[PDB]
Image (tube, rainbow, N blue to C red; front, side, top):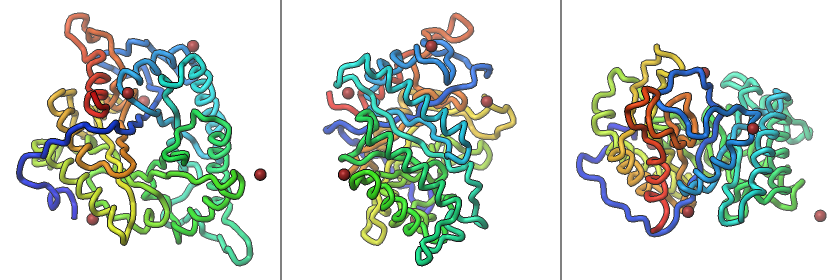
Length: 360
Ligand SMILES: [Br-]
Ligand SMILES: [Br-]
Ligand SMILES: [Br-]
Ligand SMILES: [Br-]
Ligand SMILES: [Br-]
């Protein structure tokens, strides 16, 4: 059942904010040459900078963000994998300026791209458990998780859900394996083996606007939870019903994903990924994706939808804290736009976030 099939043609129920929700938000380093309409109040910052981090930790507490997801490039690109950790260690060092109640923890958004896996080249291609032999790519796969487990074993600031370090895997539907559960159980056993029985909580991303069971064979027995990429990624052509009735579309799709993934045949948590806006035309004006302007009324309705789809994890993911390249950020802007006269969203979206996901 896809998006048209799952839209209920009637008002979305009100979901009250009664417990605190566990909110994670993607953290990024934007390209600052793009033509933004407003600018960050912390000013420009690169992957090498650290002065922005305290400001962002403050912003994050203003928003009720419990953890940031930072990119992790696979060890196959050695330099990029090194940088991924350097960035997080610089973040972690800035956490030492904060009390325990103000700490905003971290976790990784794992990118296996460098392994060169696709459908024709699975991660387990020459893996044979019975000759104790692993595909070269599976070795690297494992090493990427060992390195994460090592960071978490040694750093209480690595975000844990119920004692388990959280890992998000980008494009998890394309992590081609002849046997996804066997690959993941081998990796989990290797982590348990090396880190005193550590268990991980792995979130797998699927593409937006797609059925929640389309990629069961990639997720069932493999990951702990599934989410979609933001539904604010949408071709402006032939999407008339979806843009017009968006909040109802996402409500329909997410609550259905939460029900359907949660059946005993599958046994997977669903975690909604939300966005306040998007603009894919920033990186390239030929991107046909529709621009979602920031709209408070809409964003609150989306947050309500997400609350309608949350499960036992109590978890919601925000695309994004500061993914300015695609217009999804909530990072505090200056009070005026680049024109020097029009009011900008400022800190409005941090405050909305705390209202929509933390108990008053
Ligand atoms: Br700096
Ligand atoms: Br809070
Ligand atoms: Br021991
Ligand atoms: Br389905
Ligand atoms: Br770019």
